[PDB]
């Protein structure tokens, strides 16, 4: 196929310049099983995509929920014994925990030993995230600005 | 079991029209009939990590009038969090092994909700968290609006001042949006303007609000005029163009006001309400202040008593 | 198993775990070229290797030598129109400028707009690094931080 | 032009036994025969971003004693770097368009190397960059050591004190490892011990060095006992165990001192060299200080004149 | 004696196109042909009651490069004004009995005019009085503009940045409104916009000026893009919205830049001129800095010598 894995995940239709953030973000390289990464491959509709192939590994919930916020386009394929047993595109969650960082500098979340949490109101415009602690709602662009 | 028994009172969002109305019902009651041992034998912690004259002294007086004991601090300077670098999380964990409810004021937003994750089963009542919520204020404002106007539906309410950093007007617009027909007029410097997160909610419920450049352009139409203080201590230095009050109410400005109109203020005030207003029948900010005793006794009673019969 | 490539550079034989590290240390990903990385491939030579093929991209002599700091046994393969036109090998560079930050806190490099630079030294176990500015020598392990 | 004409002087590690020897030759010459107009029409910047009594005044007097003009600052506080937030790099960029040479003392290590990338064609003379180099100190230490011991080769040299931040002993251990058969005795607290990178260089050149816990252990054996100050300002709080002089020297100690030996100190001395040493045959640190004029004007002369002074 | 002999230099508004032209003529002359003893036997006071790197050192080097002697202070803190409470007026009264000319930088506007009423016969050269005038800055800006554009008439000049406290652009807009057909583009934040009184003068002389919200709007059109710093120290707290550079310039921006255009800055530059501009053909601010020596010693020469230098 365009590579081939017996069991594993193939995340595909990843926007150009996101694939590599995902290797850092989901810590995918702390692994020993084969990884095929194709940076800046074609994808007819939106020209240049990335593709990542983690053989014999499937993502935990949090990761696919994060994937929904970093790559809504992407598709996750569960391959068992070369059978594309499942292919799903990530829907947004209700809440994101322990990975985002509140834009409000005066949030108690910074100072204190707490896992962050955000509410995910899908606005027609974009994604508005609400901090659990300070109750400020923010644009996902603001929050995810790296 | 009453509905607010053992609840944390943190954000007005978490409360319903029914929750609010139960405290005002209770408030008017304790105002007509004192209960001086209702909380006999409970010790309560008044933890103020930020300055107060009204919320702390009203709270401690309400506690005393019901028979409770108070333990606390006026400033963390003296706590082991202030001198020995302990966390807030740890401060709340041991204080909760000592007392029956924690009343706290804190400079960072979210402190209160943080505390409830460590209070065990002990109720945390929020006295103000930086610029976020101030629910107990709003309870005594709703009580005063009701005494003066007899309705909390279809009013014309103007909020004037620093609406950005004002935890007071944040909680009040959320609570008043739980009643039908209230019309909002917002007069603030645009840099100390009302958060769009409150606005979106007023638009999610189809409530009408408008912004105005002057008090005089809505004076004639308001039931309540709610003045606020520029939160100097909260201003980012970009906003120092805003420290001195832009809209200052003077006695003469009330000339074309509804005879039923009231000027409310959370207090402290600085230059924004000229002392000559004080002598008019429209000034009602010290009455409002006195009303914090009834609203704070009601809330303590409901949180700490499974059923009240009064 | 990885891919056919017309023209570019294939750094082959990268030690497992060092392939992601290289791609992030030298800005290799920040391109618009098709890159295809194969992590944790079987080698025999070593148990596992890593490999990076950067299409339509050629590395300079110093570029390749910088790799010796993490991948000395790599083979930098120059390919022009499917023919392995060259097989280079990283020697130690004499200086690595711009990618490392001096662990010396009171070094002038942190405050002023100058690039970093370290003179590389083969000392006696690991590679020693002498800052250009403060002139202190640090082992390379250290320079790659905490 | 002579080896050092227009040449920057940033670290002893970039000079050679030949350069060091030249600078001392010229110092010997100039001490014997003054050259008052040697640098007539030259303006030098004295830029001390850090305190100095010795370096700054010996340097400026040497400039004056060759007919030069000095402009500069003893403090960064009222420079535009100091008040208007300007980078060192731009300070050096404009100051290069004005003077013929720059003498610079700075609190950061590498400040002078940074300065040579922006001084253009102008030589930057390092007057001490934090705890790294002090190359002018060393040229007057070599001048005083050769003055007293008659040689720079086959000397027994005890460096006592703060060997870690001693920019002075960094440079001096490096100047003396260029000559032959010099023996090093390093007496620091462990905390403020000689840098490894120095030791390595001694190892590769196969110089014999040894660590001692006492002046007495080495007293009978040495020729130059060179004392240093705990660089109080440069210590870590962790290091404040060592603010006082572990090894303090008094005249009694010189009892079993080799009759040729000299006590040297870069100065300021704080508590480490008791004032009774001041009357012994051995004490030479004030003569060492004065020797700064000769070494300093020999350097200036070489870097700003093509023609070797005679 | 030449037009400017013993003449005080306090504001560009007291000079004429003839004076400005003379000072540049002499600068052109002196740059070509040094006069080392021109002011041999003259002592000038360098009195900076305010920070400086550029003005103070270019001025003192220029004094030295004409054979003069400099006395003075880089700081008022250890003067008797600074510690013993003496008036400026008496500082000037005694310092007049000692030196031949006074160069003075002061934090108050009008300090130099005040100084000419007490300097007696001694010329006071204004080195910058608060946010008012900087006349020496301007003479080296005119020297650099004529050096690059070959003329001081019919120039397109964009002054970007803090136009309100920019003592530099106050003086420079006034020097260039003496020549002809110069076109002014003023790009400030509204808060720190060009003084009215300047604009009025432009209006009466019928000079065309225009306000722009972007460098791009004027980039293709201009000859001199003169950038300034937000005079952080001089801002009101109200004004602290504008502490950062609204208009920041990077090399990309120069894409549609006229090939003759030069970027000028009085310096220090903080964030407004990105270090990549430093490598463009266009960047000229360090050359502009060096041009301070020529303009500064031409001024000194004219005010202290009767006989025009040649
Ligand atoms: N044994 C397998 C089977 C599939 N794949 C990869 O997993 C994906 C399988 O999805 P599939 O829908 O069958 O291919 P497409 O239809 O082209 O992908 P899409 O429908 O999302 O456009 C393909 O990228 C393929 O390279 C694989 O690595 N190994
Ligand atoms: N058109 C080409 C030519 C070469 N290669 C890559 O270049 C590397 C080295 O060149 P080659 O001689 O073809 O393979 P090897 O002989 O195995 O190189 P070595 O023996 O040193 O591993 C191989 O890993 C191969 O993937 C390639 O991908 N595409
Ligand atoms: Zn938050
Ligand atoms: Zn360094």
Image (cartoon, coloured by chain):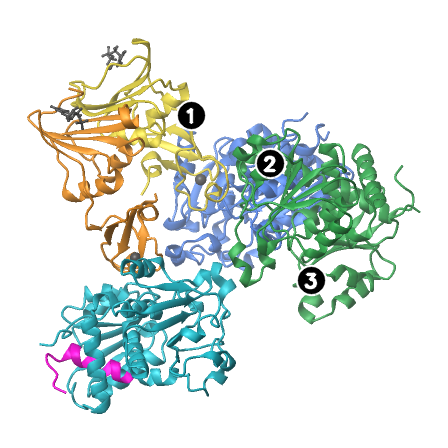
Chain colours: A orange, B cyan, C yellow, D blue, E green
**Residue at mark 1:** C94
Question: Cβ–Cβ below 8 Å for labels 1 and 2?
Answer: no
Label 1's element? loop
| Residue D78 appears in the rendering | yes
Q: Residue at x 28, y 63 (%)?
A: B110
Residue range highlighted in magenta: B293-310
Q: Chain of mark 3?
A: E
Label 3's element? loop
Q: Position of residue D195 (x, y in %)?
A: 41, 41
Viewer-proximal residue among D303 and E86? E86
**Residue at mark 2:** E219
CA gap between label 1 and label 2 equals: 44 Å
Question: Cβ–Cβ below 8 Å for labels 1 and 3?
Answer: no
Position of E191 with respect to D304 (left or right) is left
**Residue at mark 3:** E108
Q: Position of residue B162 (x, y in %)?
A: 42, 67
Within 8 Å: ligand 4 and the Cβ of disc 3?
Answer: no
Viewer-proximal residue among B10 and D301? B10
Q: Is residue B222 magenta?
A: no
Q: Residue at x 16, y 90 (%)?
A: B37
């Amino acid at each position: 196929g365009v590579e081939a894995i017996k069991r594993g995940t193939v995340i595909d239709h990843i926007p150009a310049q996101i694939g590599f953030k995902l290797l850092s973000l989901f810590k995918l390289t702390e692994t020993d099983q084969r990884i095929t990464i194709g940076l800046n491959l074609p994808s007819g509709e939106m020209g240049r995509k990335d593709l990542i192939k983690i053989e014999n590994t499937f993502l935990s919930e949090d990761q696919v929920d994060q994937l929904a916020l970093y790559a809504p386009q992407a598709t996750v394929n569960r391959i068992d014994n070369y059978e594309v047993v499942g292919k799903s595109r990530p829907s947004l969650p209700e809440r994101i925990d322990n990975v985002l960082v509140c834009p409000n500098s005066n949030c108690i979340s910074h100072a204190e030993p707490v896992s962050s949490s955000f509410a995910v109101r899908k606005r027609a415009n974009d994604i508005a995230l609400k901090c659990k602690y300070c109750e400020k709602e923010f644009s996902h662009n603001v929050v995810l600005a790296n | 079991a009453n509905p607010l028994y053992q609840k944390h009172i943190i954000s007005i969002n978490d409360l319903s029209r029914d929750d609010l109305n139960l405290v005002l019902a209770t408030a008017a009651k304790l105002k007509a009939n004192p209960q001086p041992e209702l909380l006999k034998h409970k010790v309560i912690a008044s933890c103020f990590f930020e300055a107060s004259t009204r919320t702390r002294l009203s709270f401690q007086t309400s506690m005393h009038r019901l028979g409770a004991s108070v333990v606390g601090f006026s400033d963390s300077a003296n706590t082991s969090l202030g001198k020995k670098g302990e966390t807030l999380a740890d401060t709340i964990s041991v204080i909760s092994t000592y007392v029956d409810a924690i009343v706290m004021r804190h400079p960072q937003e979210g402190a209160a909700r943080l505390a409830t994750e460590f209070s065990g089963n002990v109720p945390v009542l929020n006295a103000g968290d930086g610029s976020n919520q101030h629910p107990t204020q709003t309870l005594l404002d709703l009580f005063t609006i009701q005494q003066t106007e007899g309705r909390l539906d279809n009013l014309h309410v103007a909020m004037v001042g620093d609406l950005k950093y004002g935890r007071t007007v944040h909680s009040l617009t959320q609570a008043l949006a739980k009643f039908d027909g209230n019309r909002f007029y917002f007069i603030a410097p645009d840099a100390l303007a009302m958060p769009e997160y409150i606005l979106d909610m007023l638009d999610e419920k189809g409530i009408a609000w408008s912004l105005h450049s002057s008090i005089e352009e809505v004076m004639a139409e308001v039931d309540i005029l709610y003045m606020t203080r520029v939160q100097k201590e909260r201003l980012d230095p970009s906003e120092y163009a805003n420290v001195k009050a832009q809209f200052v109410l003077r006695a003469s400005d009330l000339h074309n006001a509804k005879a039923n109109m009231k000027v409310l203020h959370p207090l402290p005030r600085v230059d924004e309400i000229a002392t000559d207003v004080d002598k008019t029948p429209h000034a009602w900010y010290f009455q409002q202040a006195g009303n914090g005793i009834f609203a704070r006794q009601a809330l303590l009673a409901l949180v700490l008593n499974r059923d009240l019969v009064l």
